Length: 50
Length: 50
Length: 180
Image (cartoon, rainbow over all chains, first blue to last red; front, top):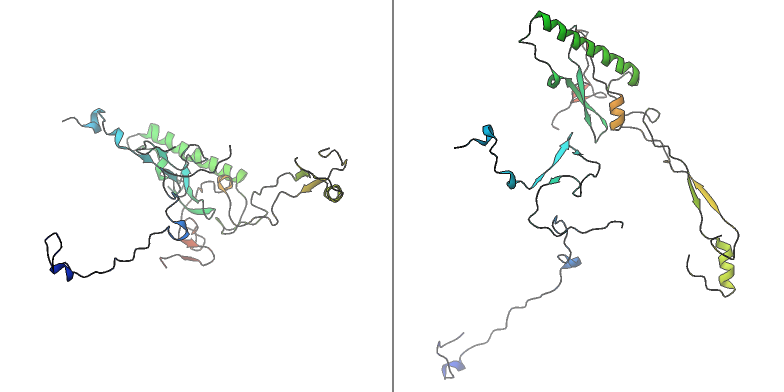
């Protein structure tokens, strides 16, 4: 809650009220999905005998 | 205009990506692992990683 | 049409390994609706000379069987891989290396040892445990299933009519299959 659009300290900015930010869990995916290109013809992996 | 069906003035040859010929609904043609792409005739590639 | 018929050419199914069903050779027919008796008689002698070849090719190559297109070919009638037995030269003497190592020698790398003259050779069966039965391959579909020249078609009592030309017909049900 911002009481005043003005910039700079005033009496009305004692009434401003704080709220915590939303929890955001950033991690690698389950079983590491999305690290390895599967099912792409342009990025197909190779297991071949030399 | 010109009728490419009748005069041989073909010009949309470049708009082909791949051809896949399968006899008898499961046997691919030419089969037999003939091409570097095993089951089809890739004509062009926009993304060439290999 | 009855005297000189068109041969029923068989459709293969590469998955089940059986013939799907035979339809007549409509796609190799020759058009003499613009010919006269000097050339219709010459083409009908080629339709009939072809049908003599197919009866001769079936008498040479097709396995004699009661039910045309069976559903489970026996293991004695299917071409089976019978390779040579695999001869394995075993690399190392097992009990001569547990005596060098217990004596304090560290073996590393690799007769083939300088400390053992013994050489073991193993001969293994390459082929399967049981002979395969049930479905013929592509090359045995070529040998059998020579296109059926069916003279005087559908004139013999029904039940003698070839129902195994039809791609819907179960032989062990005696009924045409449906969608469920």
